[PDB]
Image (cartoon, rainbow, N blue to C red; front, side, top):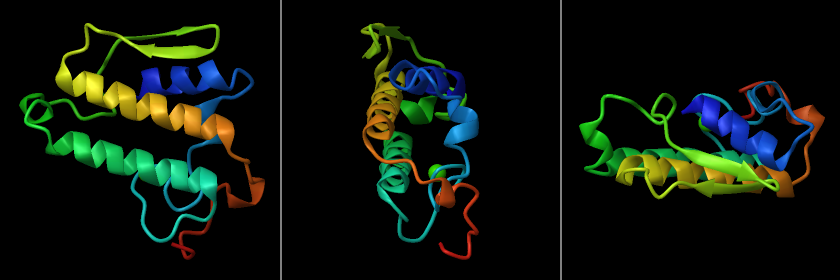
Length: 123
Ligand SMILES: [Ca+2]
């Protein structure tokens, strides 16, 4: 869910408030997304959106009424490393991996303040 995703990002970027820093960034970081990613961070978000769409296609996820945003899963942050739990059932395990991948992606690319709250006229 959103609360676990927030924590994974802070796990990799301890100085951030991910729900403030990465929401509404580019054409893809935030709800929805279309167009050509504006930079590599925006591309991390595009990949993440695709991952969520893929999760949605899984039989296992289609059984739950809960979408990725509210679907809770278990993970730990230790020494700034993220570990998705073996106790997650298939859907939750898939979503946890989508989240883990984006958090690490976010921690490896430049952050461009001029892409924050981007006019979706660029998308
Ligand atoms: Ca998005």
